[PDB]
Each structure stands twice: as C-alpha cells, then as structure tokens.
Amino acid sequence: HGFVQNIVIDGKNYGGYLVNQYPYMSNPPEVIAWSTTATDLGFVDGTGYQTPDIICHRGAKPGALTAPVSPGGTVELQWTPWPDSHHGPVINYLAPCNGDCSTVDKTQLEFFKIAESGLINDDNPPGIWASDNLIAANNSWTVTIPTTIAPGNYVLRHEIIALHSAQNQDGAQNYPQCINLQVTGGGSDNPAGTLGTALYHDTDPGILINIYQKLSSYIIPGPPLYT
Ligand SMILES: *[C@@H]1O[C@H](CO)[C@@H](O)[C@H](O)[C@H]1NC(C)=O
Ligand SMILES: [Cu+2]
C-alpha cells in the first residue's frame, strides 16, 4: 500500500494527490496529479483491469495543473515508503491529451510504454525487483521523457504492481498514479497506443505468477516498450 506524495521536475516540487488528506477536505488544492477515491492506499486487482479504475486508479479524475518538462528531462516520483513484501515491476506510459489534460476523457487515452523494469535478480527467491530498486532509491523513481515523441500535453501513468499475492487469480495489485506533463523539444513520433482497459489481463504471465519459487524469466506485463 502507498501512493506518490510528490513530483520533482527541473528543481521544484509539484505536490502530489495526497489521497489520505485531500478526499477529507472538499476544497482541496489544484495539483498536476489526478485525484483518486483510493483512500485505503490500496490497488486495482485483476477484477478491475477492464474497468475505468485501471486507467489512473479508482474513481480517478484529471489533475487541474500541468508541469512542463525540459526536452529529455527527468520526472522524479516520490512514494510513501514501499513495503519490501510488495515485490514487482515498475512500469511507465504516456498518453497524449491532444489539448488540456485537465478536461480529457480518461476512457479514451491510448498509452505507449516509455520504460519498464521487472525482476532484477533471483539469487534469493522471491528476488530483487524494480520495486526493491525503488525502495533502495529512498522510495523515488526517475522517468526520462523521450526526445523522439511529438511534444504537447500527456498523462504520465506511473505504476508499481505488487506480486506477493499474485499466485491466485486476481491476486496481483496494480498501483497506477497519473500526472499531467507538457512535453517539449523537437520530436515527431506518435507511438501506437493501448487503451487503459487493454493494458493487462488477469492471466498475463507476469500477473498470474508465484514469485516465491525460482524464476528463469519474468514477462513484464502490458504492451511493448516504445523506442
Ligand atoms: C535514505 O535516506 C535516509 C536518510 O534520510 C538513510 O538513513 C537511508 O538509509 C537512505 N537510503 C537507503 C537506500 O536506505
Ligand atoms: Cu499493500
């Protein structure tokens, strides 16, 4: 359990959607991060993959603001402390807003994968995963925005999937966190995008998996990495 408390871009903090504060507030602040109703700090499991919930987490609505990013710039996402138990991949996607991200129909966003990290080492099952890399980085993840994509407004969908329960049908725990970015620079690619509700299926080989046994490979779920 947890969520993104803060985002660092070009030497300032953009405060995240504080799901354990702003839903109790009823005149909460304008932020670059999407609001959610996920006040339990929990997840979208396999029962929700073909529901709107998977796109930017449960009952999610677009952030009011958008952060500019320098060409090939870094986005740093700071999480609440991530439990070692919650072993699994860290995956990042962009979807174009084609306009102000604050007014998009989330059910219409088409995501391309810009980065993925899975099982790093399996010397001691269940092993070292992207999630353990995230813990070792003091619960922060650094995304580099590609220089080769068309500039304009996009949603960054940033996700940990915990696999500690994933042996069981619908046991995997997806923690998607969305923010609004204004990508800048000279790129022109419009990558093939995948609907939120076509990212994952509850029987994917990297979703329905016993991590506690020796693994020879791990298939990072979702569509193919853009480069
Ligand atoms: C994270 O920072 C704290 C101090 O703020 C430090 O004590 C901790 O051990 C650091 N990093 C890791 C990888 O544990
Ligand atoms: Cu949890």
Image: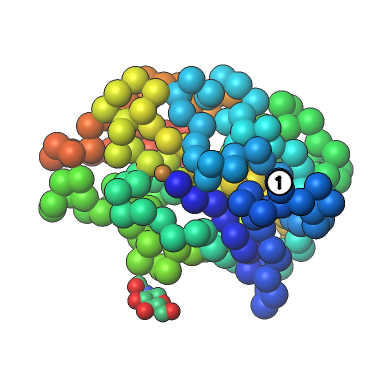
Q: Look at the numbered disc 1 and say if its residue's Cβ is closer than 8 Å to ligand 2.
A: no
Colouring chosen for the image of the structure:
rainbow
Task: Give the left or right position of residue 165, taking residue 14 as reference.
Answer: left
> Can residue 151 be seen?
no
Q: Nearer the viewer, residue 66 or 28?
A: 28
Q: Looking at this view, name the residue that lies furthest to the front.
A: 24
- Residue 45: horizontal and vertical position, in percent? 46, 28
- Return the x and y of residue 43 as percentages of the image width and height: 50, 37
Left or right, 209 with respect to 20, comes to: left
Q: Nearer the viewer, residue 43 or 199?
A: 43
Q: Secondary structure at mark 1?
A: helix
Is residue 210 among what the camera can see?
yes
Q: Residue at x 41, y 68 (%)?
A: 137
* Residue at position x 26%, y 54% in the image: 128
Residue 85 rendering spot, x and y as whole percentages: 30, 49
**Three-letter code, disc 1:** Pro
Mark 1, residue position: 23
- Residue at 69 percent across and 75 percent down: it is 12
In the rendered structure, the answer to whether residue 70 lies left or right of residue 29 reads: left
Residue 92 in the image: x percent, y percent?
A: 53, 47
Residue 160 relative to residue 8: left or right:
left
Determine the residue positioned at 73% across, 32% down: 106
Q: Quick check: which quadrant has ligand 1?
A: bottom left
